[PDB]
Image (spheres, helix red, strand yellow):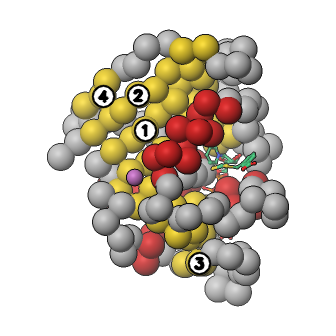
């Protein structure tokens, strides 16, 4: 099982300036629940976006995808191809935009948090992957984050 997990604005923006223009504690909790105990695969830029304090993410096989053969990710596994990272029953790809696009053919699940924020796309933004017609989704109920933004969960799946 390869799954993708991300949060996006209604515009599809997932990242800007190397970070994320929101923070939902409820989404972080759902992220930890979904990924705990499994392999997480992330691009080098996303590993850069994690503070040194919190990486590697606890209780998970942290894998970083990089073309730099000498890149050091303390506490993580650095691989040069995505296939190297899929040696486990459950692999969760956790960002960023490049690695989502790279991993989509392998994926049968997308856990998508839609954040009700009006965020026009800018040059340089990281964007969520386009899901074609093979994907079957369950649109969720709008929820209120204590951060003040409304959010909902899409759980997409395909055979
Ligand atoms: N849920 C969310 O909203 C969410 C989740 C995660 C991240 N983000 C955001 O997404 C943004 C970063 O995403 P990104 O698209 O800019 O960069 P990224 O996808 O996180 O990582 C890109 C890097 O991955 C490596 N890479 C990419 N394709 C590769 C391939 N085919 N083979 C080997 N290595 C490859 C390269 O690392 P080298 O350059 O070292 O080779 C490339 O620079 C940040 O703003 C982050 O905060 C958002
Ligand atoms: O654990 C924390 O305290 C913490 C606070 C802020 C941000 C993060 C990164 S989790 C993530 C970011 C992109 C893909 S997965 C972690
Ligand atoms: Co699990």
The CA span between labels 3 and 4 is 32 Å
Where disc 1 sits, the SS reads: strand
Above or below 75: residue 159:
above
2 and 1 marks in contact (CB < 8 Å): yes
Whether residue 37 is visible, yes or no, is: yes
Question: What residue does disc 4 label?
Answer: 137
State the image coordinates of residue 111 (x, y, percent, origin top left): 43, 38
The N terminus: image quadrant: bottom left
Question: What residue does disc 2 label?
Answer: 154
State the image coordinates of residue 19 (x, y, percent, origin top left): 76, 44
Q: Name the residue located 80 percent from the left edge and 57 percent from the top edge.
A: 51
Question: What residue does disc 1 label?
Answer: 111
1 and 3 marks in contact (CB < 8 Å): no
For marks 3 and 4 on the same chain, the one whose residue lies earlier in the sequence: 3
Whether residue 11 is visible, yes or no, is: no
Where disc 2 sits, the SS reads: strand
Q: Name the residue located 35 percent from the left edge and 70 percent from the top edge.
A: 88
Q: Name the residue located 53 percent from the left edge and 25 percent from the top edge.
A: 114
In the rendered image, which quarter is residue 29 located in?
top right
For marks 1 and 3 on the same chain, the one whose residue lies earlier in the sequence: 3
Front-lying residue, 92 or 54: 54
Question: What residue does disc 3 label?
Answer: 77
Q: Residues within 10 Å of mark 3 (few under 14, many from 20)?
A: some
Left or right of 37, for residue 48 = right
**In the displayed image of the protein, which residue is found farthest to the bottom?**
70
Can you tell me whether the CB of the residue at mark 3 lies under 8 Å from the nearest atom of ligand 1?
no
The CA span between labels 1 and 4 is 10 Å
**In the displayed image of the protein, which residue is found farthest to the left?**
159
């Amino acid at each position: 099982m390869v799954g993708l997990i991300w949060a996006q604005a209604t515009s599809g923006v997932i990242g800007r300036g190397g970070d994320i223009p929101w923070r939902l504690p409820e989404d972080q909790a759902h992220f930890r629940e979904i990924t705990m105990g499994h392999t997480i695969v992330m691009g080098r830029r996303t590993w850069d976006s994690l503070p040194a304090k919190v990486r590697p993410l606890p209780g998970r096989r942290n894998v970083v995808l990089s073309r730099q053969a000498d890149f050091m990710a303390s506490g993580a596994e650095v691989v040069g191809s995505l296939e190297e990272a899929l040696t486990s029953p459950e692999t969760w790809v956790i960002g960023g935009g490049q690695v989502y696009a790279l991993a989509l053919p392998y994926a049968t699940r997308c856990e998508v948090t839609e954040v009700d924020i009006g965020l026009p796309r800018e040059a340089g933004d990281a964007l969520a992957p386009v899901l074609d017609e093979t994907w079957r989704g369950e649109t969720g109920e709008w929820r209120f984050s204590r951060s003040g933004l409304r959010y909902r969960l899409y759980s997409y799946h395909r055979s």
